[PDB]
Image: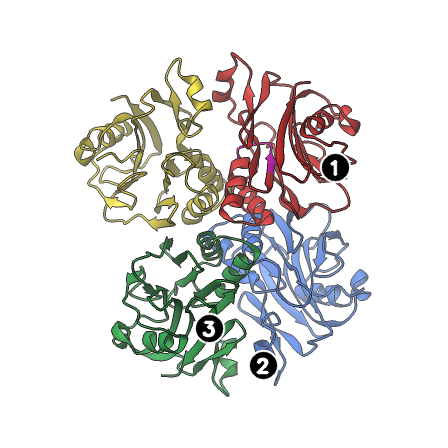
Chain colours: A red, B blue, C green, D yellow
Amino acid sequence: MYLGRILAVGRNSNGSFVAYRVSSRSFPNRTTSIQEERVAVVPVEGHERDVFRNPYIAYNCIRIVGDTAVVSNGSHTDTIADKVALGMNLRDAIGLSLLAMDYEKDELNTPRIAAAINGSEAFIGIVTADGLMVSRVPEETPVYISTYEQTEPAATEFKAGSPEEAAEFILKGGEFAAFTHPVTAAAAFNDGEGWNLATREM
Amino acid sequence: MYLGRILAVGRNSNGSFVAYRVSSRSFPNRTTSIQEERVAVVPVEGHERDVFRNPYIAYNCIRIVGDTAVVSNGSHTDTIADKVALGMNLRDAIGLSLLAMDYEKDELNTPRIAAAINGSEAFIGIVTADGLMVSRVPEETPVYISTYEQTEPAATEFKAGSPEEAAEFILKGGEFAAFTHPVTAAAAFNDGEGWNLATREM
Amino acid sequence: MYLGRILAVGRNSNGSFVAYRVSSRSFPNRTTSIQEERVAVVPVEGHERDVFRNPYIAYNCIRIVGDTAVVSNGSHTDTIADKVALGMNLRDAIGLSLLAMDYEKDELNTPRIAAAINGSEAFIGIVTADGLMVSRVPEETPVYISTYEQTEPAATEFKAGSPEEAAEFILKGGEFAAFTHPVTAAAAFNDGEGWNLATREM
Amino acid sequence: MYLGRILAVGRNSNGSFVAYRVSSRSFPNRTTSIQEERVAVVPVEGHERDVFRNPYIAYNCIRIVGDTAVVSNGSHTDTIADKVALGMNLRDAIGLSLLAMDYEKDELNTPRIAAAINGSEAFIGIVTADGLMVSRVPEETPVYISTYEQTEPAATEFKAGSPEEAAEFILKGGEFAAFTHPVTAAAAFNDGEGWNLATREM
């Protein structure tokens, strides 16, 4: 039931979205700082030195580039977002980034997961010690994936009509309530009039 | 039951192998020409002009580079084999090649499939209009994948103790007997003393 | 003075263009067949079997994808063109393709060269046994590059106001008159109203 | 005369080496912390918060993976080093990483530069808004490159017979004495018996 970092992507009757959640046992001292077209996962007041021992705990988890929302559990959020801003299709932007960045070199070979959505398409991917998988997000249902256990996209009836609702849901809502060690979350939602960011602190 | 081109990869109690089979409705006039560390799929006597109308029917389906055997349904066999000969790990050699080459631009957006095996590892991959998937071949069982229907690796009790047996099997043996439109096949087998090539004409 | 295959790209007071020329000592029996948004280099009547001994002599040298013209000395013309049609920027479309395809495995490790131009940008690149170089085409002057000798982009006062003129020029015009073993040429020119193809037979 | 970050790579009569130097106007408050097969560029005591405003000032500038030394002006040091440890040749390890990571998104589109050397080969590369260039390091002379001005490899008579000498030299030695705003440096040297790390504080 410990999935580590989790992300969800898809469309509802209310709009499209991207949701991210940090689950952790070793670094509970982190929060999500919202900014202009970007949400970063950063250390809490006083724990800013934690990044020099573990370089995987600080990074942008959500980037908004034009009509596209990008989400991931690491610095590859920028790598992917930059390629989209430069013109690369989603499938390749995620594929190229994950292939090059690869899994994280920690005690668990923590996979790098990501997803991206624009007005008409969405892809989700993961890179592990055993492979690279980037796949189209089904038009029928939203999906989620995590660094541990659920290392394959899985369907989800994501309920939300705003970024704050989306963040809350991946944090405590529905099936995610069961996944342990919640730390913090973030999300981007597009009601059809643009992307809006929001966060939630357990 | 029409899977198009098929390939299988894995290890037996007799050794490791790579098997390839052409299934076709439109171009039954092709055969497999064996050569030095390479097996090509070529037009039969007199049909050599077929390659100028359909550039996807002629290509090397098997390349042997050192201790590694590479198999695929297209020219990416060389792209992958060359990267292995230059030093790239299997996962990345297949991933990079498929990501760059992409699915074939024919009436069916025919996927590009591939696999590679050396003395200790094996990977198999596919790239389609909907995604890119490269995955480790399980140590437990051999696997196969095709351009149509079986676009995900699937387990198989591959029986063979030589290249000619392997080629025969993917051509008519076991579960492959059911897959229609057999045209020609090829294979590479390593009994632990090196790679050996062979072909079979229905 | 033997540069092998040559390509030029850039803009004039008459428009933008892409020019390609085959220089050869071993296979003079080839011509350029023009088609819908594509120019192929193919064997002359009766020499169609030459492609089974040397797989680098047959390929599309020019592809037109929307507002972009792509040129190269090999099958990577399609690899690059496809990525542009799927959404990849020129710099990356050429970079990714050349990095993956790499230099040709013939007696000379013949480099793979390419270039692409759209309404506002143009890049040119080359991949050899010693490196990978993709660079922006200067707005000031057109440039050319070849497989042998001139393995770095070089400035050129390309004179042409149509595809047939462009093809002629890289074939016999200006500084190219000196480069030996002319076989055949092709070109694409955009007077600002779209791309037009043409060829020239010595 | 302000080249920004600089790196040098090559071989002497004393051995092979990799040298790195930080030149800066905006963040002089940084130092080089040496570790096990790795040299990081980190903020000085008390300036640890500087990394949350400018994510390009903290990173490993040198990684030692087996018989290979890797150097770069950013986090791509790890991206490249990891691919080498996984089996990728130097040319491609640098090419793939730079192509994917791309230039840094700061006020100056600061290029990402890198180099790598093993017992028999060495490559150096750079990726900018205008291109991607990865090239073999000449056997004849060592070379250097920087983020600003010298964005092309340039020859250098690098004098050093140890890591501390190498670090000193790129910091104040020879032609580098003229390049302004020295902050800190690091280097790896192989006298033929393995890689050794060292740093120098102006």
Q: In which quarter of the view is residue B70 placed? A: bottom right
Q: Is residue D56 magenta?
A: no
Q: Is residue A72 magenta?
A: yes
Q: Residues at marks 2 and 1, common chain?
A: no
Placement of D117 over or under A110, stated as above or below:
below
Query: In the shown orientation, is residue D40 left or right of residue A74?
Result: left
Residue under label 2, please give it.
Answer: B48
Q: Position of residue A196 (x, y in %)?
A: 62, 32
Q: Which residues are magenta?
A: A70-75
Give the amino acid type for the residue marked by disc 3 in the picture: Asn
Q: Quadrant of the N terminus of chain C?
A: bottom left
Placement of C9 over or under D43, stated as above or below:
below
Give the amino acid type for the residue marked by disc 1 in the picture: Asn
Q: Residue at x 49, y 78 (%)?
A: C34
Q: Residue at x 63, y 26 (%)?
A: A198
Q: Residue at x 52, y 64 (%)?
A: C65
Q: Which mark is residue A14?
A: 1
Residue under label 3, please give it.
Answer: C196
